[PDB]
Structures are given as C-alpha cells and as structure tokens.
Image (cartoon, coloured by chain):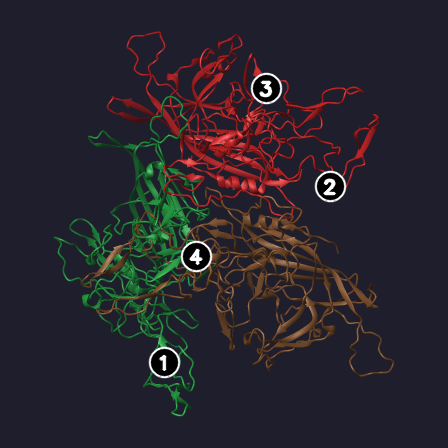
Chain colours: A red, B green, C brown
C-alpha cells in the first residue's frame, strides 16, 4: 500500500482518509491472567473489579480528531448544520517484525522476515466491547506521530470483594479465525453504519418560554387566585406578563448537578470534595459516578463568568499526557451554552410543584424540586460533539432503553464498528533435546510495527438561513505567539509536541427553536 | 531502471538526459519545529523571520548546468539564438535504506530490505514554493558526484520581533497522498511547460540612438532655441548631429545602481560598505536588498576595464563551496555588455528633464534624474541566462504584475515544475511491554540513497545571418594548464573536484536591433 | 410582476434577486438647463465645471449591498476566494402616475390611469456615463426602504472660468427611441458581462522578502563592500541575514501618501489641512485630488494602533446621511492590511537608490525616494471590494491604459451595464382658446412610483486549503446591544432606520504568496 491522508468535500458527503504508524509490543509474555481489585484498600469497595488480561492488542480510532484536522473541522462547523457517519474502510499493511537481542552491553534489533502477526475483526460482537468507554490508546491527532497499540482486557461479573462467580466468563481469543500477516500481506475491512439521525450542528436562537407573538394576548383564561371571600378570579395573559401564557411544551428533565466556577476563585467554597458532592448512581450493592449525566446547560446568557457544572462537562488535554492530576492550564474545558433554550441550567432548582391540598383552613403551599424527570410534552437537546471527543458508543444489549443517545456524545449504535485485535505470534526459543511434556514458556523477544489507514465517509447537511444579520462563527484570533517557546496554536511547539489549544464544537449556527 | 545521461540534438528540439546519485538523512529526528529570528541581535531587525522546519526533503534541479555540459552548452549558444523549455520527465529509482549501529567502537551499516521512503509531487502548489529562490541543494554539475537532498522549510507571515500572527500557516505534509518505495519500486513524474517566449540568445549590433540612415536628414524641424529678442529658432537634424533626430523609441527604465570596479583597484573608494550603498526596497516596516534589480548594462563599449555594478550582476562559484566570504579568485563574475544597445549603463545618470517653467525673467533649467521609470514607448531587454544560473521562477499569485520576467534570469512560470518531496519513513525501536499513551519518540538510525534521472525537452531557434563578416563565438583558449595541480579547465583537478573555470552565457550572435 | 428577493447558492454560481420601490419627481419643470461654476468664489478655480441638467432620471444599483445581505455576504467571504459578475436582468413594473392638486388648504393626490412614463437603456454608450463616479442615489441596503431616483446631469469640456467651448456637447435625450409605460406595462432588460478576472478574495500569508527556504544559503555571491585598499569583497547570503538574498521579484510601485491615525489622538499633528497635504494630479491647468490612489497598505503587522493613510482608504456611512461633515462615530473606515505582503505601507519611504558615481575621492551616497513607479519585475495587488462599495467602473475610451483596474475597487469594464433613464412624460394644462405659437410651459403637477427588481448572476471560486491550523473568518461579536436604543447590529434600530455597523471586505482566507 501507499500513504494517503486527505479530505474530499462533496456536496452532501465528505471523505476523510488518514494513515498512521503503530508499534505493537508483546504483552504478558504471551500469557493470559486474572486481574481483580478487592475493596479492602485504596479507593474503597466501590472500586472493585474482576476480569482478565490478554496478550492481544487492538486499534481504537473512535475520537473525531483522528479523522479531521482543525481546518477541516472549521470548514465543517461553520457551513454545515449536521453530520452523521456512513461507512469506513481500514487497511493495516507494511507489517514488519523485529527481534531484540541484549548482551547487557547494548541492544541489537534485527528484522525477521518470516515471522507473522495475527489479526481479526470481531464481527458478531462475541467479545466484550471496550471501545465506547473513552479510555486512552486512540490514534494521535497529528499524523506524523507514532503510537502504541493498547492491551486488551475486560471485566466480568464479580462477587463480593472482587471475586469471580458462576456467570463469569473466560474468552480464549485464539479460538477466533484470524489472518496471519507477513511482509507483503495486508488486512482490509469494510463497514457500513446503520441509519442514525444527524447530529444537530446548530445553536438555537429562541427559548421555549418565548415562542409566542409578543404583541398579542391569549384567548385562554388563567386562574389568578381567589377572592377575599373564596371566589375564583380570572386573568388573561398578555404582553405585560408573558410567563403567564399557557404553553404546549416543557423543557428538559433534570437531576440537580452541583455547580462549580472554573475561572473565578471567589465563587467556590473552600476545599469541597468532588467525590462526595458528585451525583452517583448505585448498582449491585455499590455506586458509581453519574457523569456527565444527561446534559444540562453549563451556563446561560447573563450568568457569572466562568460558571460551569461539577462533573457536568467534558474536559480534555491540550496534548496527550499521563499526568493524572493535570493543571488548569493543561486542559480544555468545554461548556454547553448552546442548548440553553430547551435545557435548563443544572443546579438551578426552578421547577415548582404543589405539596399539599388546600381548603378553608389550609393555604396552598408549593416547593422547589431537586429532581424532575421525563413526562409527556418535554423537549430537550443532546450533548454536543467535539473535535476531541468520541464519535460513537455501543447501545447495551437489553430489553429496553430510553432515548439511547450516549451521554458523553456522539452516535448510539446497535452494531458499532467492530473491535479489531492483533498480536505478535509467539516464536519459541531452542527446546531441550529430550522430550518434555510441559508447555514451552521461553520465547524470542520481538515487536511489530506497520501502518494503518482509515477512510471514513460522512453525511452532512448544508442549510439556508434567511436571517438578515451575520452569525457567529469559529475564528482563530490568538494575537501573536512566540515561535521560540510555543508555535502556531493547533501546531507543533518548540519541543516538537502537537498542541490542541482550545476545545471546538459543532454548534456555531443559530436556528430558531 | 538503468543509468542514462546524454543529449540528442534534433532540428528544432534537443533532449538532455542526466542521472545522479543522492543520499537522504533523517532530518530533525522525525519532528517538525518552529524557527524564528528576532531582530534584537546579529544582523538587525530587517533579518527577522518566522516559519517551520520539516522532516521532509526535496529535489532541486533548477540550475542549467544540471542539464547541460560545457560542450553541449557551447553547441547551443554558438549555433542557436533562442531556447525555451517544453517538458520534463524525472524518475527516482534503486532506492535502498540503510541502518546504522554504533557500539562507540565503530559504526556498522546494514541494509534493511523492507523499509520504505515516502515521496510525492505537489501538484496543486499547496505548499509554499521554495524552488525559485536560488539557494543551494541543486544537483551537481558533474554527474559522477554524489549530493545530499536539502531539508524543507518555509517562512510565513510574521509580527514584530519575528513572531507568528493569525494569518500564519502550519502545513502537515503527511496529509498529502504519497507513495512508498522499497527496493524494486520507482517514482515517475511527467510535466509539460506552459507557453513561454524564447529567451533571446543574441547580442545586438545596433543602438537605439542610431537607427537612422546616417546620410540623410529629417523632414521634421526641431526647436533650436530662441532669438536674442525672444523669437523661436528652428533647426533641421542631419548627419553632422545625429543626436538631434526625433525618434520613435526610448531605452530601458532604470533605478540608479552604484558602480564598482572588479579588476582595477584604483577605481574604487576605500572601505565602502556594501550594505549601506546597495539599493533597497522596503516592505512591511522593514527593507530588503533590491538585487540584482532590473537589468542594466554592467559596462559599455569604450569603458574602463573591470567596470561593473554593485549588486547589479550575478556571481557564481567555480566549484561548490560553503566559504560564505569567497576570494575573488574563487568566483565567476558575469557581466552584461550585450544589452548596451537598449539598456543604459547603471550608475550613469544621463536622462535630463525640465525642472521649471520659463518666462521673460526666468531662464529654463534642467536636471539629471537618479530614477526614471517606465513610460510608453520604451524598449528594453531581459537579463541573460547563464550555464550556472536558474532556469525558471514561479510568478507570485497576485492581481497584477508587470513584465513578469524573473530578475535573476530565466522563465517566469505561473505553473512551474512542482516541488517533489521525500522522507525516510520512521521505524520505531522496541516499545515497553506495558502500554503507554505517550508518543513513541525513539527510532532506529537510518538513511536512504538511490538514483534520480531527469530528462528535459527543449525548443531552440536556428537562424540565418546575412552579415558578411564572421561573428564572435565562445572558444576555449587557456593556453596550457598543469595536470599536476589543476587539470583541464571545465574538468577534474588534481584533488578530484570539478571546476567551472569561467562564466558562460547565451548571447554570442549579433543581430541588428 | 411579483415581488421576489432571494439568493440561490449553486456550486460555482450564485443568483441574487432583489426588488425595491422608487418614486420619480418631475425635475426642472420639464426643462433642460446649463450649469456652471466659475472659479471666482467659494472653493476656488480648481472647482469649476460646465454642463447641463436634464428632466430625466435614472437607476443606479452599482453598490454591492444592493445585491447582498450581511448574511449572504458572510457566506460568500468565508467560503469563497473569488467572485466576478456574469449577467444581470432588471425589470421595472407596476408603474402608476399620480397627480397633485393644492387649494392651499391641503394637497389632494389622485391616480391618473392613462398617463405614461418614458424609459430607455443607453445601449451604445452615447450619453456621458455617470455611474462609475461613486455618487449617491443608489438603491438602499434594506429592501423595505423607498428611494428616490436621481436627476441626470453631466459635464462637458470647459474653457477658463467654467465656460463652454466649441468641443462642448449638448445631448437631447428625447432623440432616443424609448418605451412608454402605463399601468400594466413593464420594461425588461438583459445584460451579459464581458470576461473579467476573479477578484482575489484571499489575504496573503507570505511576504515577498521571504519566499526562500530559510535553512539554506544561496549559490549567488554578493558584493559586500571594498577593502581598505579598494579591492572588492564578496559575501554569501544565508539564514543569518535573509535581506541579503538576491530575489526575482519586487513589491508594488508607490506614490508617497501622507499618514494619519484615526484612533490615537496623540499621533497626529495639530490642525493639519487635508486639502493642502493630499496628493494631487493636475490636468488642463487645474489640479484634482488623487484619491484613493493606487492602493498601498494602510497599516502593517506590528504597527501603531489606528494607523491609516490620509485619503488612502475608503470610508462609508453606517446609515444613509446627508451630513457633509459626519462625526467619527457615524462612519465605517476601511483598512487595507491584507496586501501587506506585496504592497508597501504608504508614507513609508523605504526604497533606496544611488545618487552619485563613486571613484577614489568620492564615497558612494544613496537616498530614499518619495515616488517609485512601475518597472519590470514588480508584483502588486488590487484594492479590496467591500459590501458597501462600488461593483464596477467604465474604462475610459482612450488609446492606452495600464492595468485598468478601478482605483476605488471592483471590475473595470469596457462595456459596463448601460445607464437606464426614465422621466415623467409631460401633460399640459388647459391651453388658451386662441392659437399661440409659443411653447406651452404650464403643466400638471405629477409624480410616478413603481417597483424595480434586479437579478444578477455571479461566479465564485471555492478552494481547498491544506494548511493544518484554522483560519480567521468574519464573525459577529458585539456582546449585548440595547433594543431600547439601537437594535441588532446590521438591523433596524429604535427609530426604524437601517444601520450597517462595521465595514466588511472579501479577504478573510490566507493563501501563501
């Protein structure tokens, strides 16, 4: 094969080709193993797990910025109001296996021509599907970078203290038909996405509470109170009070999510514990963070600067890092302000409901609600997709699901792109000259490398806006930057590392609600 | 492929094939980087720049002596009065990649059969075009020589102090479809030049100020002065004074360029600073040398020996050298005396113009002009092309340009031959046995080498001169040379280096103006 | 006919339909008249003119914002790098004539069904062409607005003191075949533009003084000075000093234009007279402002804030006004910073040239030039087109012209869209009952009104940029505005007037030079 990265913009379609270079170590000395964590030490009992490690490794292209460049992304989001995937093609080729030898003086790396690697795609979704979990190991943003393929592992059911049970499964991955690749062999795979709705690539220029003609007043009469003697009073909503209007629709449901201010130091309580104050959902005797949760507006218009939600937003790294506790200057923190029309600000407990039953003696009382869930007549909007975020997720296999759109973002798929696994086939060292029945555990040290190209077909919506005035769009203004320390933003810096300077998202075009 | 260098002289065409051997290092450890120079130190603020370095490298065949030999060039310039390019074919083949290993005792070079190199031609001119700038890295004059491919880099817009701005661009070159070459693969490219006018390969045997029949006198009456009483006087130009003639045409425009004498020591002022006395043109707050400028006659007939213009001529090295301050015996200094018919000598301020308005009291006054630019009715001639000089240049992409002939020489092209880039594809070293998300920065040390053949098709004008007497032509008379120190001129010397002994140019045939 | 305004974006084409409502008064009581201004009083002798007034009136759609809306313009300039006109169709219809009667108590307006108006297009350009002069009378920006058709008048040759001469022409416009329009009649006209080059809709990301590979150094040797004894010294330009490089091309020509600072009060001299310090060009004994002149960069990168040129830029009104001395807050002042790559900043006198001839005694001297005109090897860029500016101009009918691009902007046309004239046909009042030979000068007071729709076809260039990082684009960020005083920018304000908030131009996309 050959190296081709590019994009081709057609009218309703766009094709993004990109190709990388990878390196595959031998994981676990060609051995499976059990893994668990009991809840006795460390984080606690909620952190327990049980599963297996596998000598295999896999490709993960799930994130968007694998397939797009900051210029191609800008071309998408200013012009087009929607996108969905159509199909993908991936090809792994130019595989070459290298053997390592050490005399303690130096390493000597040689190229073994006849050794192979094994690769297969999991067509029927027989193995546990780890791709939709937004973990690391994805292709790099920048094509000149060389990346390392992750090791495959999974969790099964667990008992108390992170132990196996009867339902726990063990999967042998050598029991799957696979293809062996030498130099001069390649692996190709075709895939076609199922029908999904376009992601809404447009911000909304109206609110639900004002859909009305503001000059008029209703023919529907309201209940304005009671008399001093107890007689009912009526009122007609009009342009003086538009909150009085009867309405057909209601905004999004919510669970109350605590607020936190990223910019302003003086808006946050001192020394809050994010583990205690985060929303949880419990299952099977233990409870896990509910994050990000169902999307709420992080901030609305006319709100404090820096307002956000605690574990309510996505946050990314400017450049790939292992830090585990990154500084505020090393991260890109997204904000959802574009859904503020249909989606109430999380941590605002506005919704009011009647808590008693009136009569002569008892005055009616109401109260604000911390959690208000779905009822007929509600409209909401999904979380935005970002250049740095996940493309898809696998809808769990279950008897029911409600609005199966992934909470982190992207496209819920029942048959997502399959998970493609690869390993270095083992080559044994010299056996003894008398037969031994035991397994032969001594192998030659080796690793693999090659290229992988990924071509993906997308479906876009181009629109016609009849608003007169111009619209906000994504522009790059940093002023000046210093080539002696940090290069062009969204470019290579002085040390050679690629830096994504700020988060980007798809909603720059306003459309009336 | 096979090794073929040669020339084939057809009637109106000539075909020049030549093939070389190159070596490609790994540049920058497979990393991009920003580069700049602030104006705080060194040369000054006018020297500031900003841009990027690239792991890629490229082929530059632009100079003439890549495609011709001193004998083939002589055959061209004595017989033919014009030349222009038609098409070119280049083929890079026999690529082989070699790996280097060092124990500090010695280097060990081995041949990796399965490694590749990446190569593509930039068809659409998407990357900044660095070829027309007359920098080093060109193929050698002599085919047996082995040369090194340059590293690719470019400049973008800059702010103050050599910093990036919003308009500054960063180009990822792995985003271009490319071809991978092993042993047994080759890269071929076809190109066809756009229509251009022949370069004038003829010196001119007349002057503009004498185009007339010298025996006759005009029927046009001139203004010879006024009377002692103020009455107009008339005169008829004739063979006694031929400068009095009215004329249809005027010579070339000029900016005054200072003169300097290369041969004669006693004609030059002591300790002049060439940086202060050179013509400049300023742009964007800073100012750069205007050189060579629009061509003027370096010397005319009946002028001091050694006369030339300061930064008005091209100067070359007899053999490839890095000296940065070469001695006068190491350089070939061209001289333009063949345009002296239409092109006035630079630094001669001859042109005279009226600076006031006469009346009874005021006598008419005139003055000489330092700068006299284009007006209707002017004729000039372009700078000569030399065996050692550039073939073409890329006309900038702009709304207007006036007589877009390159000031250094050759053929201005809107679609020049594209820039062809190549790099060694990276091969990683042994990764760790536990997954790491970071980019893998350790690679195997390697380099590439191969052959490249360039075949170019030319279009020539053969002429018929009806002058009776013979013409000057390019002949080789050095007398005798010493094989013990310097070999045949235009040949290998004692140390094995190729030496170009004197500059050559295309205008040896006289033609009346 | 019917009312249709809209735009249709096709791939390489876009169609803009817009329709207005106009009102035509009776000009001059149906009489021609001579007009002149002698130079005896007022502005001076340079202000003199002579010509005629005409009862006719005409349509002028020349400006861009007649055909585009701020949203349609944004859609053009962010996506497309070029535009040129193809054809236009105009239709004037629904004409109705109204008669006015006054008893001094009140006016009474009645509708005369059988009266007509006269209209013709000037196909052969027989009348003097007044459209390319950027005067008022153009269609409004906002379609709901009603506008008044201008009166037609022209200037002819003049003697001293603004008097007619033999060459002066008088044109009778009733000598042109015309069409009479009642209610139920319409006038349609087709036109097809001649071939013109696309306007460059892209800013430039490189400079002429840096086109080079910054890592390399030239094979061309320069002249670095002379020795202490008079011997020539050589030097090789390299990455330490890139201004030393020889170059093929040179920046734009210039006439020095004085600078003025719009923002900063403290950068301007006190009480300068703009009439004395503006560039002039004289003709026929008198001299007129040269403005804007050939375009120079108003400001460059790393220059004082608010820097501009005095009468070097275009300036517009935010809303149509007669003020004649508008305040700085009522105007939109354009700035040309996007040509700073090929076009030197006006009022920077950088260009340096040799003013003498050296020898032993005389040291070489140089000087900076106030005016530096076109010479071979220059490249420049035309003035930008703006949403508020003129589309085209008529190239004068003359034997020669150099780069005939209009200095204010747009497309120079030899056969521009013809000038279309209209008048109310006169209806006489009651004549006497005995024959009189004299002309009948008493008429009925009347005016006309109707609609005019203009459909124009445009040709656009969509591009592919391979730069990695995002580009600057035109976005609307005003923060918040107050509906109680000024409405949405580029929208109707509180008083009902349409306001264009800031100037817009076509160059938002960078492209390497």
Q: How far apart are marks 4 and 1 (CA)?
A: 42 Å
> Disc 1 on helix, strand or loop?
loop
Query: Which callout, 2 or 3, points at the residue further toward the start of the chain?
Result: 2
Reply above or below: A99 against C162.
Answer: above
A45 and C80: which is toward the camera: A45
Q: Distance between the residues labelled 2 and 4?
A: 54 Å
Q: How far apart are marks 2 and 3 (CA)?
A: 48 Å
Label 3 crowd (10 A; few <14 / some 14-19 / many >=20): few
**Coordinates of residue B331 in the picture (x, y in percent):** 23, 57
Reply above or below: B185 against A164.
Answer: below
User: Which residue bears the numbered disc 1?
Assistant: B212
Q: Is residue B138 visible?
A: no
Residue at image location 37% in from the left, 17% down from the top: A29
Chain ID at mark 1: B
**Disc number placed over residue C342 in the picture, else none:** 4
> Disc 3 on helix, strand or loop?
loop
Q: Distance between the residues labelled 4 and 3?
A: 63 Å
Q: Is residue C350 visible?
A: yes
**Coordinates of residue C258 in the picture (x, y in percent):** 46, 63
């Amino acid at each position: 094969g050959d190296w081709h990265c590019d994009t081709k913009w057609m009218g309703d379609h766009v094709i993004t080709k990109s190709t990388r270079t990878w390196v595959l170590p031998t994981y676990g000395n060609h051995l499976y193993g059990p893994i668990n964590f009991d809840g006795t030490t460390g984080s606690g009992a909620n952190a327990a797990y049980a599963g297996y490690k596998t000598p295999w490794g896999y490709f993960d292209f799930n994130r968007f910025h694998c397939h797009f460049s900051p210029r191609d992304w800008q071309r998408l989001i200013n012009n087009h109001t929607g996108i969905r995937p159509k199909g993908l093609k991936i090809k792994v080729f130019n595989v070459q296996v290298k053997e390592v030898t050490t005399q303690d003086s130096t390493k000597t790396i040689a190229n073994n021509l006849t050794s192979t690697v094994q690769i297969f795609a999991d067509e029927n979704y027989d193995l546990p599907y780890v791709l939709g979990s937004a973990t690391q190991g994805t292709f790099p943003p920048f094509p000149n970078d060389v990346f390392m393929l992750p090791q495959y592992a999974y969790c099964t059911l667990q008992g108390n203290s992170g132990k196996f049970v009867d339902r726990s499964a063990f999967y042998c991955l050598e029991y799957f038909p696979s293809q062996m690749l030498r130099t001069g062999n390649n692996f190709e795979f075709q895939f076609k996405f199922e029908e999904v709705p376009f992601h809404s690539g447009w911000a909304q220029s109206q609110s639900l509470d004002r859909l009305m003609n503001p000059l008029l007043d209703q023919y529907l009469i309201g209940d304005y109170g009671t008399d001093a003697s107890g007689n009912l009073i009526y009122h007609r909503a009009g342009p003086n009070d538009l909150n009085e209007f009867y309405k057909n629709w209601a905004p999004a449901p919510y669970e109350c999510i605590q607020n936190i201010n990223s910019s302003d130091n003086t808006k946050n309580a001192n020394s809050i514990n994010g583990s205690n104050s985060t929303n949880k959902w419990g299952l099977q005797g233990r409870q896990a963070w509910d994050a990000p949760g169902f999307v709420q507006a992080s901030t609305y218009e006319g709100a404090a600067a820096g307002q956000s939600l605690l574990n309510g937003v996505l946050t990314f790294d400017k450049s790939s890092a292992t830090t585990s506790s990154p500084a505020a200057t090393a991260v890109n923190r997204t904000i959802e302000d574009e859904i503020q029309g249909t989606n109430n600000f999380g941590n605002a407990r506005n919704n009011i409901v009647a808590i008693n039953q009136q009569t002569k003696g008892t005055n009616p009382t109401t109260g604000s609600t911390s959690q208000f869930e779905t009822m007929p007549g509600m409209v909401w909007s999904n979380r935005d997709i970002y250049l740095q975020g996940p493309i898809w997720a696998k809808i769990p296999n279950t008897d029911g699901h409600f609005h199966p759109s992934p909470r982190m973002g992207g496209f819920g798929l029942k048959h997502p792109p399959p998970m493609i696994l690869i390993k270095n086939t083992p080559v044994p060292a010299d056996p003894p000259t008398t037969f031994n029945p035991m397994p032969q555990t001594s192998f030659i040290t080796e690793y693999s490398t090659g290229q992988v190209t990924v071509e993906m077909l997308w479906e876009v919506q181009k629109e016609s806006s009849k608003r007169w005035n111009p619209e906000v769009q994504f522009t790059s203004n940093f002023g000046t930057s210093d080539p002696a320390v940090d290069g062009i933003p969204f470019g290579i810096n002085n040390l050679g590392t690629y830096v994504e300077s700020r988060p980007i998202g798809t909603r720059y075009i306003s459309k009336h609600l």
